[PDB]
Amino acid sequence: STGSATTTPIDSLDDAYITPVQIGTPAQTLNLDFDTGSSDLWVFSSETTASEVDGQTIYTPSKSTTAKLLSGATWSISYGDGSSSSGDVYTDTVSVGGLTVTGQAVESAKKVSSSFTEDSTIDGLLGLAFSTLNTVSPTQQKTFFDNAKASLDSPVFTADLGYHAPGTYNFGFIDTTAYTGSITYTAVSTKQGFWEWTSTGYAVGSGTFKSTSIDGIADTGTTLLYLPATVVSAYWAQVSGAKSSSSVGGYVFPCSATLPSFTFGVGSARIVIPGDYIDFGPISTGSSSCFGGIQSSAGIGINIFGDVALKAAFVVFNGATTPTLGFASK
Image (cartoon, rainbow, N blue to C red):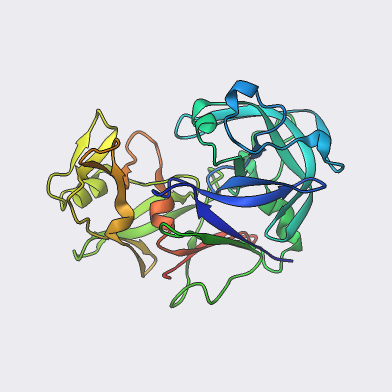
């Protein structure tokens, strides 16, 4: 089997991407944030505290003939940005882009933090990291990908995120028309439950490539590119007037700037992030200070190849017995 679904930015900045997902019988379509940095499929639901719902589409298990309470199971998750959610668990039929999993754990939110409430466009998350990170207790549950894997034509999914445009998540096949050149594969460590890999270096604009190992995670659920302070300083030093602002929470730059590109290494291959991808616009409405899309990972504890990086590539998440990651230009 295979699946193919379009993923669409939630706003003009590509802050996140939503992908329609069918849950239950008859289908209830919710728009979920596919997150390769976590491993829970959770949804706004008929159980979510009413004051914490503001415009989201909810899953109502009582209206699904295939929903079953997973008795005694609870979940609770906290994300890197400080947001969180928790609740109980159903199993139900879940389909993405024509690919169906029966008995998928669908984590129903009883509580969500303010950041989720405030984002009316995101009806929940669909985790695509390794199932070892799943938070369901006392019986840990598998991700949609892990459940689908055996049925897939090939044990892979791909992320093809757009810059200010829709893109695609495919399951079970590699669309050879979706990228240019060849795909370069690189080793993954699953020790922390992430799609963790080591970039071979970077360049800023037309500058020389610096060969240096940068361990980080491929994380579709993180907006920006978070790299070591040395690398980030080298980037922003090439932008007149750029500075790190503790009051704003990172590097800012004059909105009048033209940003240089940023290149990262994948083995001997190179992925180029155009400068425009690094512009996250005014820090507040009407400001002439703009927020940067490359930020320091210092104090996160891990480097994160988030959407800013991933949307510059066609990315293969290879879930074979020995997982690997592939990157191609596009």
